Image (cartoon, rainbow over all chains, first blue to last red; front, top):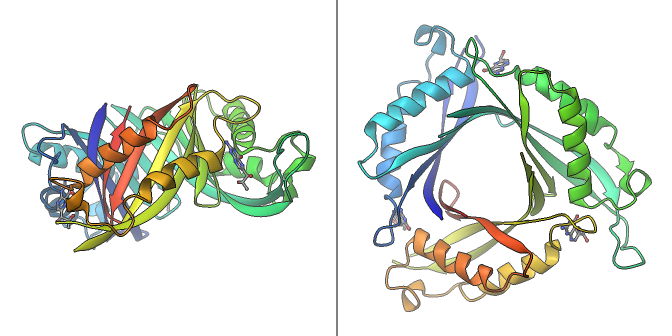
Length: 105
Length: 115
Length: 105
Ligand SMILES: C[C@H](O)[C@H](O)C1CNc2nc(N)[nH]c(=O)c2N1
Ligand SMILES: C[C@H](O)[C@H](O)C1CNc2nc(N)[nH]c(=O)c2N1
Ligand SMILES: C[C@H](O)[C@H](O)C1CNc2nc(N)[nH]c(=O)c2N1
């Protein structure tokens, strides 16, 4: 069996057409003493990354700000900050409520 | 790593499922459809969202506003989902593959098909 | 191909304050006579289990009532009430709307 904790967040950005992006992050690991990893630590890691894009024009930070590339970047940034016994499992980024990009490791 | 684009849409249809040899009472729902297409991120894209949505909505269009018991012998959520999956697969460009189809009958009950 | 039916339900419970839990259960099996498993039957099985949690003191049942442990608790009792030809595929438990645990078999 595989266990994961999920956190959902959102941020607004433009690329120009501004959107409200909904981000879902799934971190996989083992349930140790009732916890995989506390939600607040993960959520802090995630927001610390999304805040760099919040209210910005992604065309100034990304060569080509496609939802896929933004999702990719976010995944790499998250990966670099997660704790030792945990892995980035899934990243789902919705460009508005009806369209999204799912990245699964 | 796998990369997919997801497109969400909805359509409404009325129907009654078989409860033995006889039928339940007819009623309508808003169906929520989630389609996941997997492929490689080329030039920053897997597949254009709108291109996928059009393929999917042309399909749901045949079900939209219709009595499903007139289209399916047994309009269960699984048979409808299967039918949608097959229709989509048949229309997808040669560089992607149908990965997932999630059909919700309302927001409380749904069927998930994965390839 | 794999086919699953999914049911969503909700229950409120207190532990340590109280929360509104959102549960999503996915059952994998083959489609026979047009369906994997009757939606109501699963819903019955699931809500009979959640009924034992509804507005309860979770610390009376769990030494450490974390979201993960509660998810494991539910996953197990569901596996014990399921019919012979289907399998518990996934359990997603959201404590509130933006934080959840996902168990996958
Ligand atoms: C009230 C809330 O349930 C409590 O603060 C927390 C915090 N962080 C958590 N983190 C995890 N992984 N699992 C949990 O159940 C909780 N619960
Ligand atoms: C406004 C619209 O969202 C934008 O032009 C698009 C269109 N199609 C897309 N298609 C993919 N695959 N990824 C994207 O980020 C976008 N963005
Ligand atoms: C009204 C209700 O949705 C209808 O009677 C049901 C019940 N159980 C079901 N169970 C499955 N597996 N698939 C379905 O479409 C339904 N439909």
